[PDB]
Amino acid sequence: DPLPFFPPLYLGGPEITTENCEREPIHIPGSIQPHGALLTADGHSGEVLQMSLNAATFLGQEPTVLRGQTLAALLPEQWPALQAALPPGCPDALQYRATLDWPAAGHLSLTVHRVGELLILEFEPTEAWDSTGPHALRNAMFALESAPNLRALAEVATQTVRELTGFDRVMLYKFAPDATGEVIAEARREGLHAFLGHRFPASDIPAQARALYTRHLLRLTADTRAAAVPLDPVLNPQTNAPTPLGGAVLRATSPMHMQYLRNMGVGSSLSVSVVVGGQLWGLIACHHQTPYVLPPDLRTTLESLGRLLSLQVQVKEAH
Ligand SMILES: *C/C=C1/C(=C/c2[nH]c(/C=C3[NH+]=C(/C=C4\NC(=O)C(C=C)=C4C)C(C)=C\3CCC(=O)O)c(CCC(=O)O)c2C)NC(=O)[C@H]1C
Picture (cartoon, rainbow, N blue to C red):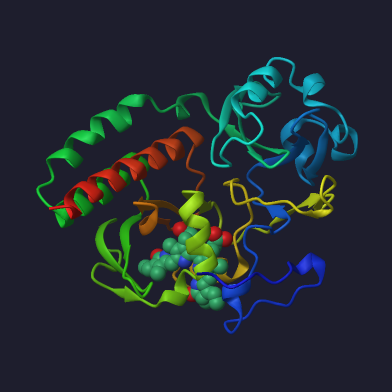
């Protein structure tokens, strides 16, 4: 049962310390990570309402010039499909995904979801060979299916995720009923210190984070030293209230957790929820020693692997 959040910093809210960090409003930071661009749009008209300040770098033109244009004008070949894919009232975790061409090498990956009457559009560069087929997940199901018990399933799952991603460290972090956690399986680069069997306090993943991770199953920090980029305007004009960014992997990470990562020597972090009968059972928690952007198709593969593992855990715990 999480505490109510305090206002964010840009609404004059308090600075976040170790005494009050269960109240940080981590879903509404008003800013994104700088490896991509974000726009928000009205869900019926398509009118562009908010843009990240770096939008020109990715889109080829200025925020001041794109704001107020409609997606029917800007994205004539995707706007109908996007509308159809995310009708009003659909789940905020449902996504639309398209690949677009741009001035530069590779393409732009476009990911869109709906929160209330607002469409949230994320653009991130992707290379062409950075395609992942459905075989990656398909072939991986095999070793997960043959694991004979829960711990063997956890060990195969961390090894499969490390093989798919190349991450330096991949853990399965399981929550206890008091919300403390334990690393129950770990695949890691030879010579990295082991976290296997280590337990952590509940405060390391505070209650409002555990709530958010029950609904939006994947989040990441691509570069634990990168400054966030503001959305402008920072509040959603539809509501004159903060924009919920829980559903956007580009959402800026809590500064408090960015510090926690830098203290562990982590350059890039990503985790996928394992949700069992609607409760958060644990996380697939990954680190890399340097900044790294896992490509969008691999992320989506990992999400699916989390849902598959959640079912296999749920099967075995009933035994
Ligand atoms: C006073 C507030 C604190 C707190 C804030 C906090 N932590 C998170 C998110 C995560 N914490 C994680 C914990 C671990 N990563 C590990 O490697 C290990 C053990 C080896 C642990 C225990 C994890 C996995 C996450 C999820 C995100 C990720 O995978 O990188 C947040 C929310 C971050 C966000 O989504 O914006 C917050 C606010 N951590 C503290 O320790 C105290 C200081």
